[PDB]
Image (tube, rainbow over all chains, first blue to last red; front, top):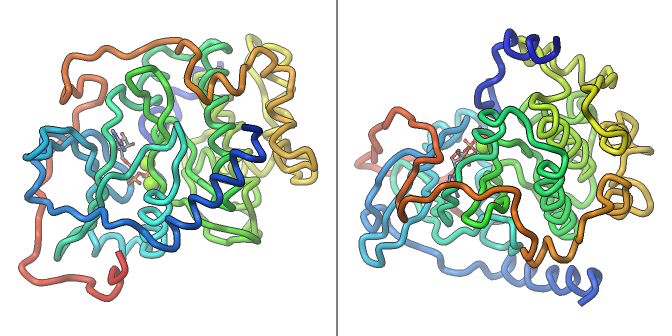
Length: 19
Length: 338
Ligand SMILES: Nc1ncnc2c1ncn2[C@@H]1O[C@H](COP(=O)(O)OP(=O)(O)OP(=O)(O)O)[C@@H](O)[C@H]1O
Ligand SMILES: [Mg+2]
Ligand SMILES: [Mg+2]
């Protein structure tokens, strides 16, 4: 599922302008 | 007041403030520093207490050297300049700015309900009426900004704060710029970065309406429409244009999003002849009393818990870092006009 895909992306926490 | 009258009047106030900025000076030793509220790529924002008045504020602290290394000199000058000149119900207000040998400080109104982000992640997702409530404010806010030829360029839940009445306050004007024609800086949090920006084209105010599309999607879906492991892969997806929606999205929501998340500028809502009115009149905003939202007469879908003036229980905890000030001036030239 997309929701599962999101979790495994590693980008569910706070996003800064630069990574 | 019609909108034309309101905005033309707004443009006149702004230009005055723009041309003769007020003396919003203060000094670091005038504020008691309580706790870190949040951090970004550039700055740390701290809850502070004015030693005199007892008033609380959010102080944004920027390291001059870091600002220079990350090449945000012109952006930081923009940030402060635009902030002290704008005036809208949902833009956080700048109370003081100043600098010392080492740092730049922007002391804002303290918005104590935390980031939209933390509520969104915890609840999981917002119902469409709930998302619609926040979306309407952003719409009115972009209308105001764009009439001033200002573009915001970093719309995300991390940059939106909830106040005591459950309304949005847009903060972080780090990428805000006055642009009457085109601009070229490759900037903007990746998930929310418009295609034209990624393609290294000259772009305009329309990038914010793309970003609105991404916001609304994330608010109703609980996750953004374009994501992947590395920022590179994300950009590929944004350029591809192919969006897939969750099955619970209403048909209206899907249509609006199709018109916001439009890779072709000639078709993107908010960039057509009718302008912002194509968004304000879209089926999904049928039940939106656009005026009443501006006057803040509409009941918010929720209101955060409050336990005092300097209560920070709606913000995550961050590791506290020492505020260092050099004994000699640094970057005197780069920030001469701050
Ligand atoms: N007026 C405010 N009141 C309360 N908290 C705030 C306020 N302004 C900012 N914050 C908190 O501090 C965090 C960092 O602020 P800001 O986004 O201005 O820093 P930044 O370095 O520009 O971030 P970015 O990486 O998005 O550019 C915000 O995400 C928010 O959590
Ligand atoms: Mg930010
Ligand atoms: Mg920023």
